[PDB]
Length: 459
Ligand SMILES: O=C1O[C@H](CO)[C@@H](O)[C@H](O)[C@H]1O
Image (tube, rainbow, N blue to C red; front, top):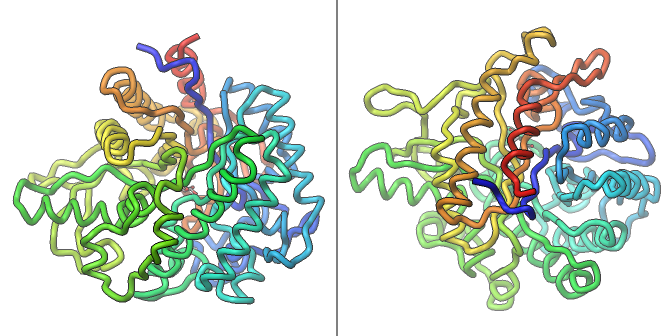
């Protein structure tokens, strides 16, 4: 069985996670630059000051992608490189724009389709200081829309695949709910407000795209949402209901508004006044505001009722069944275990629920303890190859067999990189990086994926 010729595959990265050169060519700080200077926030006390030095080694990264035979490449734009201070009235940075324009043109020359994420968490710090970023409704919406417009104008004739936001669930929960990610806020209200404003900022950017650029540039625009596949801990009504509630707090609170036109029932009932209400005009704007369903997924979880964390929807999630059996192979992060079947079930679920072509914008695995391995051992990344073997198979079945409309798959990540609060200790690349020399060494998983997609995409 083979995926249609139109299917695209490749790898994904995020600007702050790989670029480095934090103040080069006019770039000003993002909230993540600030966050990494706060003690105790990053596990290994690192930052994205250097990362994989991909801002400078952008050419090398493109050659690497080409050598892998990818059909596409997903990367994000550092907002503070394009508009350093971020605002609609702030000075635009020609050098930053040119950098990305040149990168995209190299991708075009190499025949690699660019998938561009406008926002992958690096909000310009000036906006946070000016009005609290996403916390301010009208300022955040106008500035993001202006930023999106500038991006469409600057790269739109070469880019036909846009992603507004990368995981608003993470942006809101981790950044404003428990303070684990930048800007490190902790509140039972801000996460819901930030989420609301992002849904609106997203919708404004999409309407702008469709109305002023889509016809001439012939592209599409969507949002990337994260979601694991969730399975009831047992077959009791409490567990089944808890699973549905968990899906709402993770995915439904974003997908139902954007694809169906309203916030789901449970969360509104639970959060009450803390969950903002869309006005009739906002609902209209938001409903149907995504051309394709961008999905980032990594594992499967068992769900039980009785959780005490409101950010999770008052449920308990884990990878340990009632009989003690684990879902799958352990990775470097406790919550993430290998479970291919869940990927297949999730793809079908999403296609049926939201009726938009699915693009898996992220899927990968961090080999447990790989950071301690020398390059010659790290390249034999057995567990990562097994993960991709299981997940690509789930993908093949979902489309060709089950009938789920899935049109893209991007592996996270092209390179080992800065894994946010975990620092550099968690390795997700199909390519090993020696941070002391910046030398790139392909791991065996890279050979597996190149070979698998070559053999499973119609010629
Ligand atoms: O979903 C994700 O998982 C990746 C691995 O945790 C992380 O590096 C990306 O920034 C994030 O988008």
